Image (cartoon, rainbow over all chains, first blue to last red; front, side):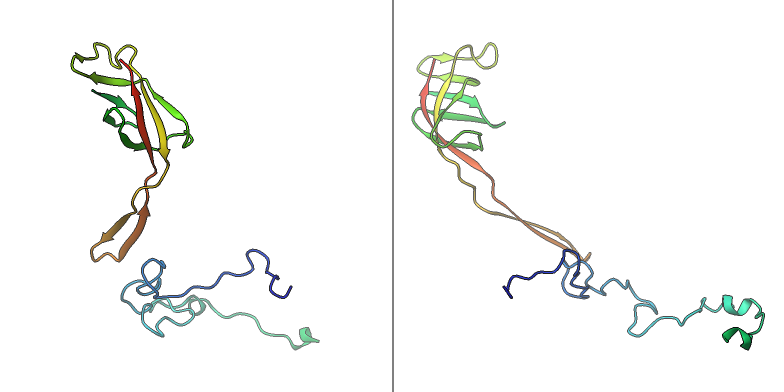
Length: 72
Length: 103
């Protein structure tokens, strides 16, 4: 019977493979569009980057303090 | 000695005792079929249709085969636009032999 067990429907998806033909859908850059920083290998912006504008976590003021008694 | 009749949206001119291929019909391969929609009957003397479909003309035909037509390959290709598509088609057909043509 070892060649009769099957998984539940919807348990597997087979993943996404990029750049494998036209009919496969996401080929020819595999869904990352045309030129640009995001299209490059290893490209992208770090967390909180807004394109040069002051990030939200920098526009706002830090407040409060940590209490050691709260951890005990 | 030939008649004109309308079967599958397209008219056919068939002589006595000849096989004609026409669109698929809901008839088994070993049963006779009737075509009372006779457009024109021709003989030594000529008879036309004052009203369409003559008056009493019928055609007796026997089904022979219910095969599929030759494969046709459909190719859609957009130049430079990263779009190609392939498809195949086999049209169903019915072979029928005309057994008798009335007056």
